[PDB]
Length: 118
Length: 444
Figure 1 (tube, chains in turn orange, green):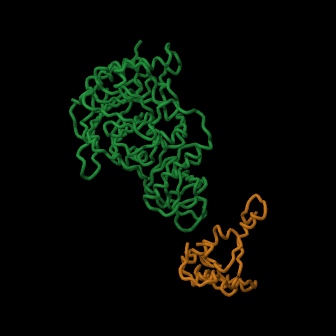
Figure 2: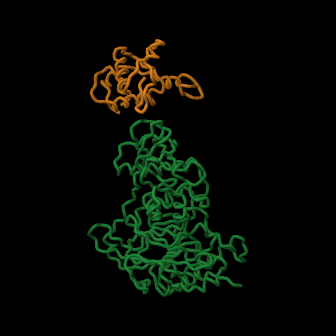
Figure 3: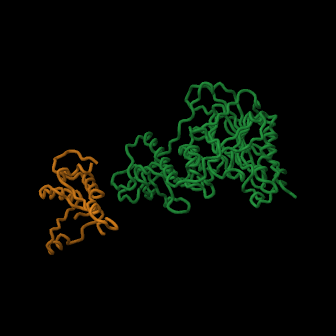
């Protein structure tokens, strides 16, 4: 978790955290949080990524909130070291498969909607 | 007992209420029928000649139309501003996008800064509608049905915050052949009904017109319906003792004849208010056979609207109050100092139709099937005659002399008509040399 710019983490958070034992690494700049992820990813090194509305919202946000704050080594989200990022999606995480539950959900079941909620 | 009383006791008679071009005296006069007068009907396939093809529409096609409408223009707007690709109105993104669509209101009322919405095209956004946020837009002119290219940010894909509203692009103007520069000066009169006072059936003004037609001996007299006003009190309560069809032939005579000496070509333009004609825009020409070999060389019947060539001089012709419509439903960023009209008319030249505003005034039926083939502008008119219940005027815009002669009649009082003087000058120079050299709106 990070913080905006006009906000400040509530007081004692880090500590109040440390009391209820929760692996919640707190970053200061979105740029921090982003690099962090990009980091975890590199060593966790997933082969498949499962999210929701991945291909239609999130996957992009990220790839932009990242080039926005020029985080260190976007390419990590990948598995093929690369210099410049295209705006371009499927190619972003090359070497890593992306499961989009929204998509596979429809293709696999009938429902009123396909918002995570339903 | 009284009828036309006030009309004929008019003293403003003959008064010029506006001029334009190069000051002219009061001695307006053309050579009559003298010399060559080339009246060529122009547009898409010769702007309709028969009654119709029908009066029954298939929703599955109106759709097809409205879509082409947007696609076409778009297709070309995209080639002009050289944009790379439009974005679906439904696909979200953080970066700025360039959508393609047509405005439209979100309810049954008066379009407004809040309620605007854009309905994309089929080809890209398979008709999705996404409301529009203008707070962040500086200069904008919008009207329902306005084919528009917008650039803004739609992140959630459920609202686009406009950042730029590309400016409409009109069509090139007509390329004069060498023959058209060899024609001499002509003077076109122009007037539109009602041609009678709302309290009488005298057609007095009609006559005055005639006389005036004679006196000044104009080369062309384009006359706009309603000859028999579907709205004239007596006509709507059917108190007339004569059949419509007749009444109309009646006036048609009086005028053809009343002006046989003049030597002026007569070009009639039908109106949706002409009780006796096909209440369907675009309308077909008028129907009449009572014509000598003589009058057949002197009168001509044309659709509504139309693109007619008066000596390599491309005129635009429409009887429908396109201006009191578009203008009733238009939104802008400025009110301090801007020319309402000069704007509305501006869209007209860029929208490429004789009535883009869609959906169309509550009382103005249209058959889009036909509308696709017979109501598009061919080239930016050299002159535009857009009658209207709105005060007289003549403004040059985007190289087009837009003229509104006002009504020959207005309720119980005297109206106006207008005249233009033409002649296409010397070939070379900084291109645009408005063949229309001057004009005057005159009371009658």
